[PDB]
Length: 118
Length: 118
Image 1 (tube, rainbow over the protein chains, first blue to last red):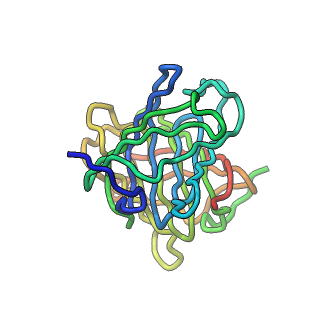
Image 2: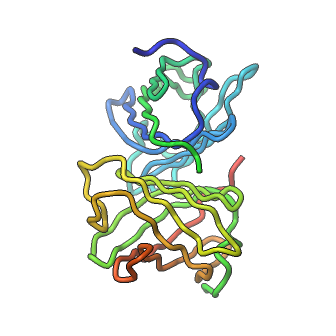
Image 3: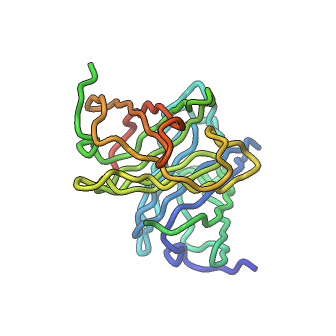
């Protein structure tokens, strides 16, 4: 089962990710965790941020292919606030992230551990 | 214009990548370059490798979703050899990568620099 735990407890490695927005649009991507560093992306945007702790974990989202819609229909670069605690297992986790400054704009994410860093 | 250069001279950061295989199947993905470390993936596989410089660069491809076809139709994990030489810019590059052990199996890749990492 999943249990509330701090994100920083996540094992280092590459994860597969699936997410759905308040607009009810879905997307899938990849996520890489190294130290407290988080980098990732899907066919249209890439994301980067640093596991906070003592700070609001901010994830900078950057769109790179506008011929593909944003799961959030924003149309520019934004920030997602990552929860300090997530529901997790040794290899699975879910979290609810919302756009900074707008709780009504959000995505629910499920992440699955794929493998350790080389 | 693109000029021949050492692949290991690529700017660290997040890259979008598009590729076509000898079988005429195309795929798209993301690629992250940190030090000599390269990590990335698409909707069905993830990859990790180390920009060598004294050894042929081996990119380890791990298939994580077998419900989606691989651009090479290998049906298992494999290794790609990454050229020490690439045709590149300060933001673009292309390369021809063959499967370790079989030059007849390969992907021709175009990579676009998206943004540097934190």
